[PDB]
Image: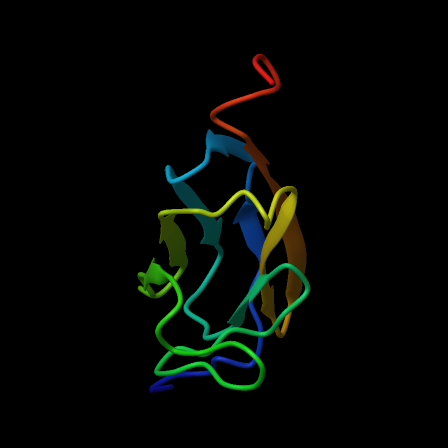
Amino acid sequence: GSSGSSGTARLVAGLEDVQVYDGEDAVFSLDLSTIIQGTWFLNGEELKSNEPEGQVEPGALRYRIEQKGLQHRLILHAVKHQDSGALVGFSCPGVQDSAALTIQESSGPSSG
């Protein structure tokens, strides 16, 4: 919904790197200069607001997206390790930024 001139926007508070253990939950957010509607990305992939598509299924992981004027956010609950060093960024017509999601393994090589 674009009531007023929502051509482009400016970045005021870019994203930030976040590292969590396997199964944990990641959180990302950013600020803008004006209202706008962009798109989120994960591991170089274009996510959907309503429902995803392609090789990935709509029933693989749980995520939350909060879009409010110049306030975006994306939390990934139960982040898998296999997706270590993921790429979480919000692409929009006027701004371009992204972050790095590092995921370490809970257990390591000890016995065996």
